[PDB]
Image: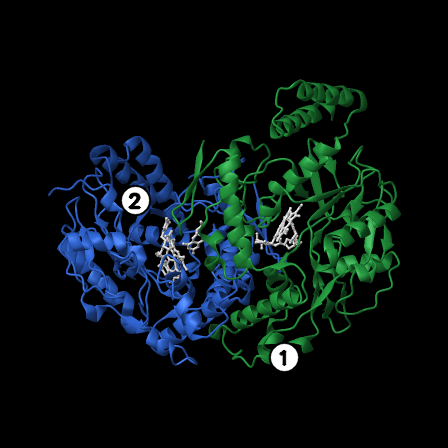
Chain colours: A green, B blue
Amino acid sequence: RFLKVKNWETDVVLTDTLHLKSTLETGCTEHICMGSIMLPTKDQLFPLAKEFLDQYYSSIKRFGSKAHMDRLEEVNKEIESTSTYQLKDTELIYGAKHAWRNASRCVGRIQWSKLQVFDARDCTTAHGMFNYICNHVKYATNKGNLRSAITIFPQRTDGKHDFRVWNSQLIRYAGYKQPDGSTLGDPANVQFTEICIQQGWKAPRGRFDVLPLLLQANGNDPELFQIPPELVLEVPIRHPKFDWFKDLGLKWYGLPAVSNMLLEIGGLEFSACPFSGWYMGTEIGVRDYCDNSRYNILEEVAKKMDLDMRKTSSLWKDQALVEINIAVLYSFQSDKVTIVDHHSATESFIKHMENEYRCRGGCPADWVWIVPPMSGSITPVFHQEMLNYRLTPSFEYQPDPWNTHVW
Amino acid sequence: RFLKVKNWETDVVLTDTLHLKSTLETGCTEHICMGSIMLPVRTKDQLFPLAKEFLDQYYSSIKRFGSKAHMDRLEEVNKEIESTSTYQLKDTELIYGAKHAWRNASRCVGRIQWSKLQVFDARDCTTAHGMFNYICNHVKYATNKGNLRSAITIFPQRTDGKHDFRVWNSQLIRYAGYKQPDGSTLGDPANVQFTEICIQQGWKAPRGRFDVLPLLLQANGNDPELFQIPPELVLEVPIRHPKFDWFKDLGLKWYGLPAVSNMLLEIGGLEFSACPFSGWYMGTEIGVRDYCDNSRYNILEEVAKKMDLDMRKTSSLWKDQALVEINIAVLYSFQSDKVTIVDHHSATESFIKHMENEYRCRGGCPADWVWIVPPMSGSITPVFHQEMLNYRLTPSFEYQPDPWNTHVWKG
Ligand code: HEM
Ligand code: HEM
Ligand SMILES: Cc1cc(N)nc(C[C@@H]2CNC[C@@H]2OCCCCCc2ccccn2)c1
Ligand SMILES: Cc1cc(N)nc(C[C@@H]2CNC[C@@H]2OCCCCCc2ccccn2)c1
Ligand SMILES: C[C@H](O)[C@H](O)[C@H]1CNc2nc(N)[nH]c(=O)c2N1
Ligand SMILES: C[C@H](O)[C@H](O)[C@H]1CNc2nc(N)[nH]c(=O)c2N1
Ligand SMILES: [Zn+2]
């Protein structure tokens, strides 16, 4: 019932008790582990609210105080009467910070308590959503000195009046399938790019076109807005040694801003809750640039490096991979845009895990996502056993809205 | 019930029904996943059903399920269990069992090869000297002058648990490790404890960086005995780099034959506590883990020094750069010396083809993503993007505790 996790590099053993508070299900059973699968009423609401308010009042050292009992009382009355309830500002902020704290797939959580929370619960239209999102983008970007932020739109009611950002991230590059059957831009975004055109966007038809936002307020059909280009900090990618590198014409944006997740706090569901931090270099250099179904540039860089591409065993892909990732880090650093390398991020995460074991009794962590997509075993997380379990408040993945929306 | 897995690079989707035949436990529950945890005397009451399940699988594989031969064998085994409290496997069953334990080994990326396994039946073995001879023969056969052949040698099964056969070595061939008074380690830090046991047992240690360890062999529950593998049988490869001529002067070498000797083979409920098996290396095993783990030979600093990389910030990716060069050197060296090795790109591509084939012909392929994905360049290999289901099938290979923790010394 009390569980041990061992680091095989250091012999450090931590004991996990926090998992015993978990409530939701993993996908795993006693007979099958689904650890590598990407996606494995009034009655229901009150225990959820109580569970949350108990943890909140506990956190401010006021558990079992009159203010605790009174708030439990007030929320209970509000639920029975209105079928839902509203979080106090203090509770919203606590809940959002804890959803990040509990995100078992996030290597960046040492930072969890420094989150700027923008309360957008007074929002009523897509133009309003656009305004709030621009302000978030500008605040978060901070001229390259990135600051973590979340913007929280109104909570779900009957489920027919959802706020949604249709974009999967606030800032991404367009994808277009061309006459010769290939893809221009980001193949990840071809479907979304066409939906944007279908709704009216005028695509400049390039390789790195910042997509428009497609915003859904109150269950209405979504509307298009172009983010002010001056608000989108992009970085040209050069290499500190290879001068030909710039000729590839690659760039990436500074602000990673996930916008398709659902924030659950105390049983309430915030279906539009765009959040942002800063990049770990491998997200761009390994995944965005080198996945075969993404920009898929390994073959081009390797040719420019004059590597023996005839046999897999020359490790040409691996050599190019490293150089591509040196370039990303160098470029962001040169342009003073916050970025973190995978060695640094993972070392922070080990320090974070130790803090969480010490101060909280554990840290839910998904090793499959935490270990970086290159150089796994030379980062300390590779050797670190992790227990994965689901705590609330949480961020949950939700279906792309186009499969859901009726026009 | 049916379970689907998706490859996110190709959108290929597979359907797993094989998991329904699984009975053993994973360590996970609906409330916790233990997928990254390394480690998450039988009665007759237990033995009959396990024997039956196995013989049913065996007889199905040969297209004789329900035959007289099948029924007679069930009866024979049943009688033998109630009469002697155990039973003996037929040769054909032992072979089938060993091949299936490899086929079922969810941590093994090399399983496309599972049906080509040479099984050496050593169940007539009685002494440690006998074990030595069988292991020498295995090493010579498997090595095949660099043209490596997969093999397993199977010693007598467990009886009362007081008479176990065990190879105390974790692999047949490994290098000694020596903790120095100043706290540094000479040779392989992974093997310091075992090296100390060997020395205590009377091994004369050369005390170099790459001393092949003696075998420490326990037969029939007796105290283990030391043997030196004839050096002419131990194929090694000096490591050099195709472009960097200074690489050879690092003084590195490795052995060609990866031969796991500490696992327990379970077949039809019988336990084979000594079952050394061998294949060939994937390059990263040596170049990534053995050479670059901080707790192993830990050569990244020195290699990076000689490469004159910028070592003042981790963000120069000096570690990543040196890592790749070292792995080039390992593959080049083995290839140049005509010793079998496979790079991690080729091995993972083959594993995907194996896995899909297994889904079609068998209804699934249990696979542990945490182990299958290589320890460098993960996402540029196809297995990174492949959803896998992990579950336990028997016959199986299982971890067992090191024998020095459990052994009753006879003195
Ligand atoms: C401050 C810098 C941060 C860094 C360096 C960072 C790092 C990362 C990385 C590398 C991933 C893996 C994503 C992928 O492979 O696509 C990730 C996932 C995630 N992080 Fe962060 N993180 C940061 C901030 C945040 C913030 C501010 C939140 C929310 C407030 C957050 C919540 C998440 C969640 C929910 C996931 C899983 C996403 C999914 O399932 O698609 N992280 N983090
Ligand atoms: C023929 C070439 C083979 C290759 C290239 C190969 C590759 C590998 C690799 C890379 C691992 C992970 C090793 C590690 O990270 O330490 C592994 C694990 C394993 N393989 Fe193989 N394999 C081969 C043959 C075999 C054979 C012949 C058997 C048994 C008959 C076997 C059974 C296993 C088992 C049980 C594990 C898990 C080891 C453990 O838990 O400690 N494999 N394989
Ligand atoms: C099917 C699916 C499920 C899921 N949970 N998430 C995704 C999104 C995929 C998973 N990895 C790549 C892509 O997500 C990219 C967006 C994540 C950026 C995360 C981030 C947030 C903050 C700071 C740095 N990085 C897809
Ligand atoms: C705690 C623990 C559990 C376990 N199941 N296995 C181990 C042994 C570890 C796993 N990785 C490092 C060490 O194993 C080294 C031997 C692996 C050789 C595998 C092999 C066999 C055949 C061909 C190629 N490779 C340790
Ligand atoms: C199938 C497998 O779960 C999938 O490819 C995962 C592996 N690990 C990952 N890890 C991170 N950080 N991000 C990802 O998108 C993935 N993809
Ligand atoms: C803690 C974690 O499970 C552990 O370090 C694992 C990770 N994946 C691995 N994968 C392989 N092939 N071999 C290993 O030893 C490990 N070690
Ligand atoms: Zn699991």
Residue that carries the numbered disc 2 in the rendered image: B401
Q: Position of residue B71 (x, y in %)?
A: 33, 41
* Mark 1: few/some/many CA within 10 Å (<14, 14-19, 20+): few
| Rendered image quadrant of residue A183 | bottom right
Name the residue located 48 percent from the left edge and 64 percent from the top edge: B350
- Residue closer to the observer: B244 or A356: A356
Q: Is mark 2 within 8 Å of ligand 4?
A: no
Determine if residue B406 is in view.
yes
Three-letter amino acid code at the position of disc 2? Pro
* SS label for mark 2: loop
Q: Horizontally, is B411 left or right of A160 in the view?
A: left
Three-letter amino acid code at the position of disc 1? Asp
Q: Position of residue A243 (x, y in %)?
A: 63, 79
B162 is higher (above) or lower (below) than B151: above
Q: Is mark 1 within 8 Å of ligand 3?
A: no
Residue that carries the numbered disc 1 in the rendered image: A243
- Residue closer to the observer: B258 or A6: A6
Q: Horizontally, is A144 left or right of B289 in the view?
A: right
Name the residue located 58 percent from the left edge and 46 percent from the top edge: A110
Front tag of 1 and 2? 1
Q: CA distance from mark 1 to mark 2?
A: 55 Å
Numbered circle sitting on residue B130: none
Name the residue located 65 percent from the left edge and 59 percent from the top edge: A338
Q: Position of residue B294 (x, y in %)?
A: 40, 58
Which of the chains bears the disc numbered 1? Answer: A
Instruction: Give the quarter of the figure containing the N terminus of chain A.
Output: top left
